[PDB]
Amino acid sequence: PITGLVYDQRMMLHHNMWDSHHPELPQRISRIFSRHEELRLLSRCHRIPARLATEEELALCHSSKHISIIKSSEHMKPRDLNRLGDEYNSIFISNESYTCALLAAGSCFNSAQAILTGQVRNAVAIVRPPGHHAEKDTACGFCFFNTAALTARYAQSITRESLRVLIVDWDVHHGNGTQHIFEEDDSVLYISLHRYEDGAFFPNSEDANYDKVGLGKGRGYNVNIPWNGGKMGDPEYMAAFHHLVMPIAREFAPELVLVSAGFDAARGDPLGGFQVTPEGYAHLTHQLMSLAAGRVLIILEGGYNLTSISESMSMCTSMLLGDSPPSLDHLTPLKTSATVSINNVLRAHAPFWSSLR
Ligand SMILES: O=C(NO)c1ccc(CNC(=O)c2cccnc2C(F)(F)F)cc1
Ligand SMILES: [K+]
Ligand SMILES: [K+]
Ligand SMILES: [Zn+2]
């Protein structure tokens, strides 16, 4: 019963040359790592090394053009870096960005491989830059390559093509990139919880609404749980897990669970405006550990309050290590719009999941 951990300070080298205070900070990953040390969690884990994703591995989800452009940025002077970055929605690029994104993905490949070969039962990946906004053909929202989507395909490549992978994306933002990559795929179930505000929240697309259920053979295999009009927290996320995430996940019966674990829905985050607590994230982790025979890989996405994300991700690792869940607060009645949101998703996915009927 071993928990893997991957962290490599080389991923701090990616940085914003023009705004050194940009929230997607190098110290995001070092602060999470430090908190694991501080809580004496690090020594309880088995350290998994980082590695570079190969270009062939990036092609599991990304176009050769997109790979080539980000790859070319390694050699750019700052004037191309700034101008190239401004071509995307919410991206900054430094000469080290490409290599850091490669290390983020390869770190997660090594972690999935250790899980799937039985070297560890579960694992945590303290990586940046994030991935879930990255599309097949473009970078977006601080993300260059879709780490979680790539890891799902890498997992299938070392097991069998039809390996059932569940991606639970609890970053406060919609993982537009991962939704699109798997939208026609029934082997990868995508479930995202996200602040939506009727499309008035990044990434500002009705793609994130509850009625986007997947396409083709993927109908039913894309689950968007969109929050509107309310400062959501533990009671809403627990209710969403009880009524939607866990019933659908159990019916799907995944063989591997990946968490796109952004911590920007956390109390204190400067961007998300929500109030999920560290003990809330612990309970969400503990629930997912009941799936896939415990084969869970937690992948850092967003989250910008350094103290909040360090406490929150550490509590997740504590759960992976087998510690008992901390006690939740009394739990207020749901925000009424949260009930509306949950019921809209239930109506949207009742055609496909009998456990919701
Ligand atoms: O991945 C993410 N969260 O996990 C993520 C991705 C994209 C955005 C969009 N941009 C902004 O909100 C924005 C606008 C102006 C000034 N500063 C910002 C800031 F950097 F703070 F976000 C936000 C969050
Ligand atoms: K999300
Ligand atoms: K899907
Ligand atoms: Zn986010």
Image: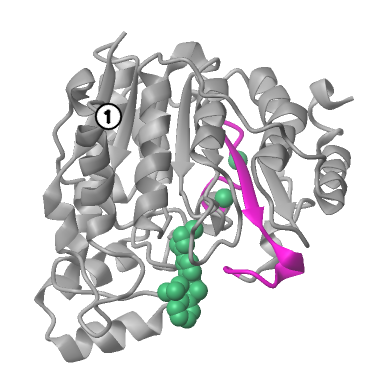
User: For the N terminus, which image quadrant?
Assistant: top left
Closer-to-camera residue (94/170)? 170
**Residue found at x 25% / y 21%:** 114
User: Disc 1 on helix, strand or loop?
Assistant: helix
Q: Residue furthest front?
A: 330
Tell me: 357 left or right of 183. right
Kindly identify which residue carries mark 1.
Answer: 111
290 or 315, which lies in front? 315
Residue 36 lies in the magenta stretch: no
Tell me which residue sits at (40%, 58%) in the image. 305
The magenta-colored residue range is 180-203
211 relative to 161 in the view: left or right? right
Disc 1 within 8 angstroms of ligand 2 (CB) = no
Q: Quadrant of the C terminus?
A: top right
Image quarter for residue 284? top right
Residue 191 percent across, percent down from the top left: 62, 40
Please say which color scheme the image uses: one colour
The location of residue 153, given as percent across then percent down, is 40, 36
**Does residue 198 show up magenta in the picture?**
yes
- Mark 1: few, some, or many residues within 10 Å (few <14, many ≥20)? many
Residue 55 appears in view: no
Residue 212, horizontal then vertical, whole percent? 74, 52
Occupied quadrant, residue 185: top right
Q: Tell me if residue 36 comes above or below residue 287 in the rendering.
A: below
